[PDB]
Image 1 (cartoon, one colour):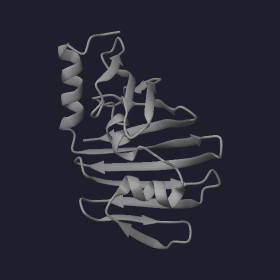
Image 2: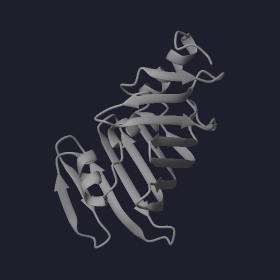
Image 3: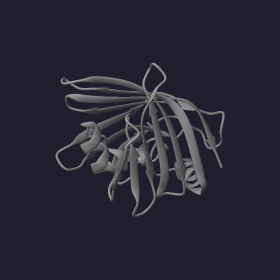
Image 4: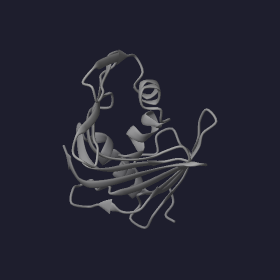
Length: 177
């Protein structure tokens, strides 16, 4: 599609990186061979290192909440018990049994490529596809629409595939500033 060597792609990244707070909510799906999980999620990020993730099952009951600031990383589970750790990704993986690429996702959910070099853009000069390998995990990210009600526009539908496992994200809407 469009070339990464384009002023509009740089402008889009700039606008996204210039935001100080991001907020979205929607549906989440983790599908592997061992389990198929569904949930609604609330995501809030302030800056590049402070964020909050809230998950509720399809029945409406909250399942867990992850809060993170540099150094302090907290998670509250179904039983309302609070666990602390120093790494959000590791903790999520360990406490839920799912290898969610949280670090990479914090960039990708925003329409940014993170540390990924292999990626493509659509005709609107926005990320459409990413290919990233890290620690034996070759994730294939595919964007399926953006929500242009905000400027800059933010991802509406995302697909992540790591061989046998697949992550699906559906954003209802965004609030940014």
